[PDB]
Length: 128
Ligand SMILES: [Cu+2]
Ligand SMILES: [Cu+2]
Image (cartoon, rainbow, N blue to C red; front, side, top):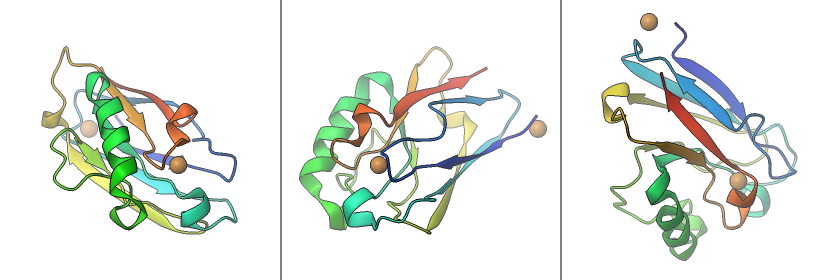
């Protein structure tokens, strides 16, 4: 099965899809994030961040406080299962993570931690 997905975040504060499935036979999984917008990362930067559903709010809140130069992630945040860097227009970044980091019977959310963006840039990552 495929173990990679291409995700885009645009100038309108949207991911192209808010639902990702990781097949259980994948040993690793890769997210290739790109930004087809024109806006720079300080105005409309995006990352792709994965946590449990219960941890998302805390990751987002703490990332807001840590600021742009930390890519809006609190340093040493063990709740983050995997993430890309924060990117602006025309940039790209990929993250590959081990599927063994996804507990069965845990529930996972994907989101961008640029402040405010998770109002729209949030969704589910399903292990099946
Ligand atoms: Cu395979
Ligand atoms: Cu964003």
